[PDB]
Image (cartoon, rainbow, N blue to C red; front, side, top):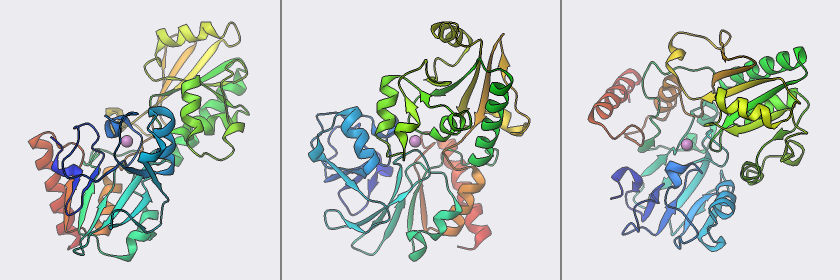
Length: 341
Ligand code: NI
């Protein structure tokens, strides 16, 4: 049964709740972003309204094959009425097309649902700054003080330098980047751009990217592998056995792979900086793990929440155990007591 944290009080609106069958009472299913835990259940045989961003719209139409009539795309930063309730979509700073939703209830209650987000100070000068938010449905993926990681800009700077050095030392080296969903496109586009290449990828991954409204994208990507010295692979395939395999397939055009695995947090964040990173090396294949996050660090989350000063916080991540639930409530109480709300 659909959990209470996927339902919006006093509306017939649900958020990211496509895997339960029909939810009784629901006039409208919101989708925050095209990631599979959130969309799970959507297919060509959905005949209820889905509201989402334009980009998420393109992905539902072309990858899942949902029929045009059930997809309602909304623009961002625009007051819109949806079944007689004012709503706003705001950039979540997560993956392409990912949004937060502002709900203005008839009773006067204002509710913010973050979907998945990476909190940023630029959000403090958006439409959010204009009025009080009473209820916050919060992405708590990294709600614990151990979770630190660098800025996205720091990580891209590292990647660009690594790749450029290695290719300028050895012009027959190949850069591979791992992938499994949308998200983190800056990693491979930054590398490609320093190296004067397009990025080469399978037909399914090329199709996924052509839905994202990226500017000049036709100049940045291709399905012709041979012509490209930055390649995308399934993240499953980023290991020595699978890379070796792939190094064969190129047919004596490259002698060395330099690969990146953009991970979330890993326990080596607790003891090592970004300037001091090292790969695993089995011959001519090296594999970097780089902690490029599209979720809030603990301190980023804490700051956005202490600015917002919400009357109530409902977690949407790590809610399946009583220990996580209890631990999270503790942080919300400290935050509130520190900040005086
Ligand atoms: Ni996500």
